[PDB]
Image (cartoon, rainbow, N blue to C red; front, side, top):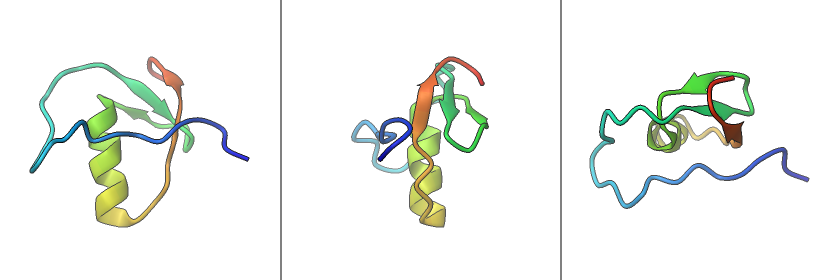
Length: 56
């Protein structure tokens, strides 16, 4: 099934803000905000989900 939820890019056209609102990815890595995880998934064609909010 899934071990979390899909990371959204919040209608960001080119990039994300530097808002610090950390999410824990299903890879065990902290992403500074959800949107850099969404663009990371777009650029690498990966499917890291969000386990939960907060740092890992």
